[PDB]
Length: 340
Image (cartoon, rainbow, N blue to C red):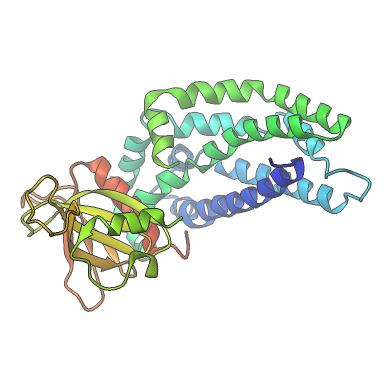
């Protein structure tokens, strides 16, 4: 249902957002490691960010060519012919950096080595000195952002196929076929790397308000306005333990609300009473700080602290470090949404 031109328009918007993400990664997250030569060697940086810089250069070059092509496209053509933009680059093996990148970032021991780099002497303190939120963003959000190049390059393979099938110009079609061919090595190479179980789980990990109303409907004792009257999207739904509370609360995370409920699944109700599976306990408005907490003999491990306006802090605990990571990823992203 999409024309060749729609795909190109969609792609230009995608690569512009992507380029912005690469910039964020380079100027905001990576620059501080590069700046502290004493704490991180060239390799340390290399082991975390890989070919990120080359990929950024390739991307700006790709978008630039595509932009000129479009502007220089007269009414004589059925659609701008971008086949050549891709073919010229693929012929110079310009996409090779992505295979190397994917290999470095999706290696099985990536995260462990990443953490060791953040926990070695003076590292955590240096990251905190960069500014509020940097240490948390680096630890729980950066590893997700670092996957962006993989998603982006994988989509290229699919994009080129669709363009080839939809091209209305024989010369353009030919260029596309050639680009596809010249990229077969990079593709099978990335394919092997991405199909391994761990990588596959990681990629899957970071991959109509009917749901919002369906969720409120199933929550008893609602307070304040509707979910739709302050939220625009649904982020997460998991389980956590409130340090101090008696029962593990089920939680619905929206961009505007973190709803903490109690599960009454299967428990008896009086006739005429609500049949909703959950009971509202805490309704938190997302527009305040989020702090990380170290494990405590207090039985609470994999915990973090939420700080509300003029309210008392609340501490939650997750079932594992993996669960805590998913929550901090979403929560930290929400707190610094303006930057991210």
